Image (cartoon, rainbow, N blue to C red; front, side, top):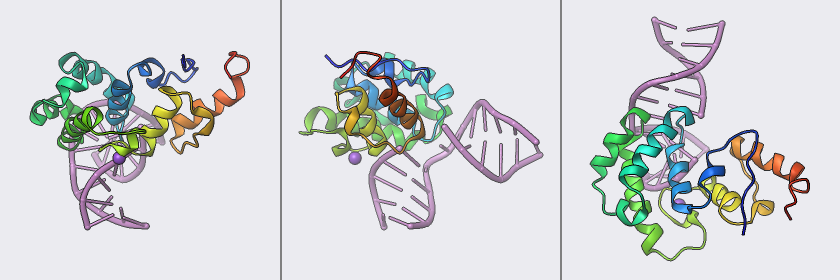
Length: 144
DNA sequence: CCAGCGGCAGC
DNA sequence: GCTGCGCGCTGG
Ligand SMILES: [K+]
């Protein structure tokens, strides 16, 4: 089974990879928002909405109240509910096919959730740091 | 003090 | 191709 390695850069994707919905929600939380502020709120969100199954039933106004100190709160609250609906009920191969996930979320999924990191060409700086480091260290970490 | 900064959809 | 969304943190 593909386990992405921990890096000296401590991307939150390294800990969330096991649950692709939670990883992708985290990428949404990090859209133009510092991890220092977003990630504490992420845990409160996941306490209230532990799964896509329940998040797709949420009132976006309740989600936006949680997102308020992060900015982009009405936008992302509506995104999270629709994303969670499509994640479960739309046929998809890569999550870029889903509302709210672009290249950054998709590259994140393809590096962390599935074993496709060698095919990914990130433009995100933090993904580039992790991905460059992976190419330089994957042999030492005994990964293919 | 406060401008700059930490993705995505819809055009 | 550009713009709206958007708070709190950063640092001279
Ligand atoms: K998409």
